[PDB]
Amino acid sequence: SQPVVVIDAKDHLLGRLASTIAKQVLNGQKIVVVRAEALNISGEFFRNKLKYHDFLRKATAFNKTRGPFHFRAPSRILYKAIRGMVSHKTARGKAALERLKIFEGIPPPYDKKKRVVVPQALRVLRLKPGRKYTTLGKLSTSVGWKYEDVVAKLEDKRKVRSAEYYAKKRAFTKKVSSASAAASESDVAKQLASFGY
Amino acid sequence: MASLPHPKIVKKHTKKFKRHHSDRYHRVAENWRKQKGIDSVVRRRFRGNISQPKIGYGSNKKTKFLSPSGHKTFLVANVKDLETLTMHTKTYAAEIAHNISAKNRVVILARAKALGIKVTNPKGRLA
Amino acid sequence: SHRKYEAPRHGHLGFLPRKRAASIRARVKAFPKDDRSKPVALTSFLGY
Amino acid sequence: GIDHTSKQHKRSGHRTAPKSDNVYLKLLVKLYTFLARRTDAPFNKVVLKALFLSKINRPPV
Amino acid sequence: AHFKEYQVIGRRLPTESVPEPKLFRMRIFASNEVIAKSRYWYFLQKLHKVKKASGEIVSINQINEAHPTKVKNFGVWVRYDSRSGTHNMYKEIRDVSRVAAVETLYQDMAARHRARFRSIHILKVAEIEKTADVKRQYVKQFLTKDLKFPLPHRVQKSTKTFSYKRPSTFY
Amino acid sequence: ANLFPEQQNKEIKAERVEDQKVVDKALIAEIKKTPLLKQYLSASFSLKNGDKPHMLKF
Amino acid sequence: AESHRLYVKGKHLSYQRSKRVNNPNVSLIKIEGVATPQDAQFYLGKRIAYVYRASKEVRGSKIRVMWGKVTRTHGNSGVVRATFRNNLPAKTFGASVRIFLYPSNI
RNA sequence: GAAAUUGUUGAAAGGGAAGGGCAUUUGAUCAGACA
RNA sequence: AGAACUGGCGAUGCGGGAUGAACCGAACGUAGAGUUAAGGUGCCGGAAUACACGCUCAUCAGACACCACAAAAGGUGUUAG
RNA sequence: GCCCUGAAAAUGGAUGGCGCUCAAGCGUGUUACCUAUACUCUACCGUCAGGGUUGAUAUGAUGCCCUGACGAGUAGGCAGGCGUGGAGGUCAGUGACGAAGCCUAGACCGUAAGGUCGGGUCGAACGGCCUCUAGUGCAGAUCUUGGUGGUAGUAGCAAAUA
RNA sequence: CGAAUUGCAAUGUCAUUUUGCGUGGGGAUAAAUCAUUUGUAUACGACUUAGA
């Protein structure tokens, strides 16, 4: 229902998120995935690394600047997964992927905004407890992504600046709750509670 | 020239049935010719390829040869041909031939305006 | 079919795009690491 | 989609009118169709289906 | 399937030499009378000299359960044909009804041995009466005193695709 | 004729208004026997964001 | 006061189709809030409009409308079918149509 | 005084072809006006 | 390489098997509405991230018969007997 | 029963792809749902068959009307038709107030072959109907003749002292 | 106080970028290419140089 949808990709599964996206962004929703470095993917790290190396093996022999462009960052990994779910060789798919913006970390326009969660992609709900999973940051860093130590220095900063906001808002919230609780016994409110409100 | 007993003229396949590879080659005209080949695809009616004429596309017998005005067309070259339509005014429309002189077109038009007949090419050779 | 007699490659595939450089002044794609204790001093120079 | 026992669109092997263009024969047929239709006598139909016949199936007596 | 239990009486066809032949009875598990009557002639035709044509079916009656709101330990003696050889098995189940025990026996047999309905013959189903003849641990662990356990990891279903708070698995 | 010929185009009469005043005064009489209803009729219906018409009543 | 609307917004998903074949006569509509065929049966017969722009002002407006209706449901998730006077142009895949309540049964 | 082929003007389109079938939008054009 | 019976292709498009002369379904006038076949319902892709009992974690898993490959011999790895 | 080892091949690569691990995998089961030129209903065309109608109206039955069923198709057979050059009749046919021809993302008719109209150009003969007749209909034949293109403003115009 | 006669429904328009023109209010006063030249360059382009 929202015009734009900001998605925290922490503790999310890759394909199970990307299918949901690839349908919504084809149906016409502008979607902004954010904090893609903390994404998760099933199976063990060595297994996923073997699969990525099998993907790196595939390059056009006669000129390797023509072939599968192996993007090493998590945003681009997820973009690959979505683009495989989308008909990107058409205007429909190109327009659809123009409605998508993926980021590592949480930049300014989307740090002061509300983030949501796709529950049919969450690791904690889908995976059996005890199974091994994999983190996309460690994976990308293992295959040649050089900016994990930077988004970390920025995310803790964002987090400090967010926790102080929460620390202020929580006090404002208790004050408003203590101001509104002084009217709950009133006939304006025990007449509302007869309607559920 | 009211002529309002006719019912809902429908036309199956209002397109023109062009020949195969009339657009690729200038020698192959657009006039329809069946493809008698053996390794053909129009002859075998594959998917995505063009549509061929059949009698299934044939028009209703009540709305055959009618122009959308509800009339069917009769060619006249002179007044003697018009006077045949003095009864059948609400069914036949008097198209004038392509070879008549402007001197005689006005005679025909004037006679038809009196007989109530409807003409389909009355702005012809007029100036 | 295989080569009758093996021999190494000619050239180096890492000095590739064996083209003209984009500027006559070559650019330093890498500087030393910074020791955040030593005195402030230049790292390089350009001469003729 | 039907499994046909019989051949479809099978003309009856007979001729329901002459091959000739003789006006007077056509008129005789106009008469005997009327009689064969509006009469229960099978003479009329026999004569009719005989008026259609070739010169070799209509031989001389 | 959604099974049912049937009681099928059958009879080799009468003759002047023996116009009161022997009625044979079978208690069969199946989804409908049709395949029940088919299985009756499958088992009887393994033991006695008769067929459908050379025989008839007298009575066919559904057997409903007497105490379907009672938990029972159903011991089950069965035989199944594998890809290489034929074997027997005994399994205990803890369902309330004979038919339900069968329904969950066909299933876990197909799981653990990849044996289909067409391979399995259910020989005997026995309600065990006392809590001392049970010998299978996966049943005995539910025959304890003051049995209690939790469901730790809960997963709430969702009718909407976007949610605005991280879930909790607490029960 | 699309330039206001003024042949019975826009003139509201003074006969309907008595028949309008006779019913509404007898009807507001029944409305004012219950509260918050003059305001109800004065308002206008609109669907908000979370409104599911197949789920809500009238 | 801030809201004035009397319609439900929905999306033109696609045409009716098999795999590798489509029927542009029939279009598929995703309505908001709907999740089942029951509770979509309410929206049957209801009119639909696709409102778009054009540069040639005709009859005193740049906005133009293509009308249609809802005919029947789609399988298990609250999608429906629609049939317009003049079928929709396929660049509207992922565009907002508006379903009215004009033929009502409440 | 045709066509192939070509020049100028005008309209339109164009990320490693073009052309074609079904459906519709948009632009042009024609319609009949039931006058 | 040579035969028997039926069916089909050749002479035959259509839905499915990604693709395919032969497989599955089903055989064709032009159109509308409805229902289905074989096959399928995460997304590409129209259709349940539907329900239920179980097995499996594979450092080249496995995944629509014809079909596009797999044996003997071993594993307290696990499950049941 | 599942999984692993056995099980090694040559451009980079294929459960169709992404991707999936209490599956989006395997075995089995229950409903719901999608959709083929198939099935059902209706309209329309055509063919085949059966029947009614010369009461006699437009004497025509070449037809008109009702009813039911059916429609794949190479080689090949038959039928009904379109078109072309000339011939015999006929419209007391068109026409220098402009015949024929040519151009026309301008119109109409027919399932189609094709016909008809408007406009522009042009300048002297040409059509419709009933029949006759044939040197009668082209995308091809490494077809014949004539003409024309991309290649392409390209290869190249450099032996013999200047 | 008025909102009626848009006559039983027909988007019954406010969004959002770009662009031109005019009104009036201030604000700002240049480089590149060719041609010539150089040879750290060079098949031609290009590169690198110099020139009131």
Image (cartoon, coloured by chain):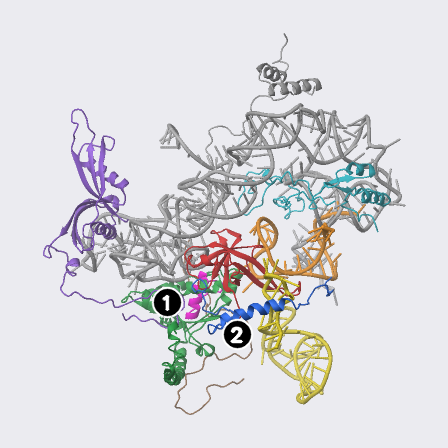
Chain colours: A green, B cyan, C brown, E purple, F blue, G red, H orange, K yellow
* In the image, residue B49 lies in the stretch drawn in magenta: no
Q: Amino acid at mark 2?
A: Glu
Rendered image: mark on residue A119: 1
Check the image and report above or below for A88 versus H19: below
Q: Position of residue A160 (x, y in %)?
A: 38, 83
Quarter-wise, where is residue B98 in the image? top right
Looking at the image, residue G84 sits to the left or right of residue H1; the answer is: left
Check the image and report above or below for H25 versus C33: above
| Residue beneath disc 2 | G2
Element under label 2?
loop
Q: Position of residue F19 (x, y in %)?
A: 60, 67
Q: Position of residue F48 (x, y in %)?
A: 48, 70
The reply to whether residue C3 is visible in this rendering is no
Element under label 1?
helix
- Residue range of the region highlighted in magenta in the rendering: A65-85
Rendered image: mark on residue G15: none
Q: Position of residue D6 (x, y in %)?
A: 48, 28
Rate crowding at label 2 as few (under 14), some (14 to 19) or many (20 or more) other CA atoms within 10 Å: few
In this rendering, do the residues under marks 1 and 2 share a single chain?
no
Residue at mark 1 to residue at mark 2: CA–CA distance: 33 Å
Quarter-wise, where is residue G34 in the image? bottom left
Nearer to me, A134 or A145: A134
Nearer to me, E139 or A54: E139
Q: Amino acid at mark 1?
A: Pro
Nearer to me, A32 or F22: F22
Chain hosting mark 2: G
Q: Residue furthest top?
A: D61
The reply to whether residue B9 is visible in this rendering is yes
